Amino acid sequence: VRMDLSRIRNFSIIAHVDHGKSTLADRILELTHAVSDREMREQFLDSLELERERGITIKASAVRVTYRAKDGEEYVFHLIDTPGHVDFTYEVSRALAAVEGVLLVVDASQGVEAETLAKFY
RNA sequence: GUUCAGAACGUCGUGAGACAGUUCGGUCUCUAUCCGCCACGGGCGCAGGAGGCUUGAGGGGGGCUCUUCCUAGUACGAGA
Ligand SMILES: Nc1nc2c(ncn2[C@@H]2O[C@H](COP(=O)(O)OP(=O)(O)CP(=O)(O)O)[C@@H](O)[C@H]2O)c(=O)[nH]1
Image (cartoon, rainbow, N blue to C red):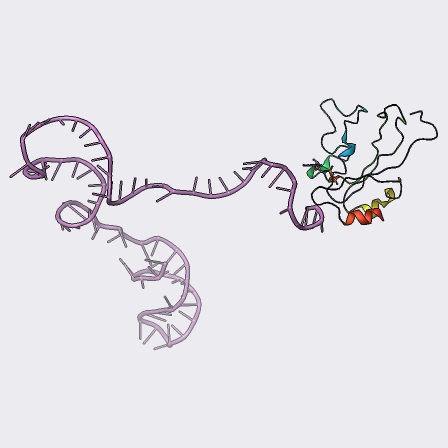
């Protein structure tokens, strides 16, 4: 994106089990994409469709934004945040201490849990 | 089916013959009367003569099951 040196960042939205770790970065980001009747449907992000059995997303790869800032940094920051629940963390940890910071909304129902403490460690 | 003659082995029986030992083909009788019943009645009553309507103790009857897909995939459940 021509965005030479400077800018960019590292943020991730990690949380406990079943928390819609694929809600925030779903769409309608103004960036314009995923449509034509073939929208990324519920739980986009490639995946494999096979997970349709229960939308049990394995990992979160790719999915980067571009423009959306009221005339600012434009777009400089990752967007990878594998979901799950202590089922791939360790193995997928490779992405844990990869991008600084990690977003994630607490479940209004179950709420915070273990995955929260361990996820912070 | 075995529980009658056949014959059959097998086998006991000195044999005649037999065996809850099996096997193989071995005649099944049916014009209703009372009660009983499904109706269908014929009489008479039910008490000014009729005709049409009906309400109904009383009996019946059938008196069903499940999947799917609901809300919401939420309470809880660490997920499942
Ligand atoms: N009623 C309701 N449903 C929500 C809410 N947020 C997310 N969801 C629903 O719950 C589903 C799961 O949320 P989401 O975290 O994005 O998916 P996931 O839990 O990460 C499944 P995986 O971990 O495999 O990616 C979503 O399909 C979405 O429809 C909410 O605030 N209210």
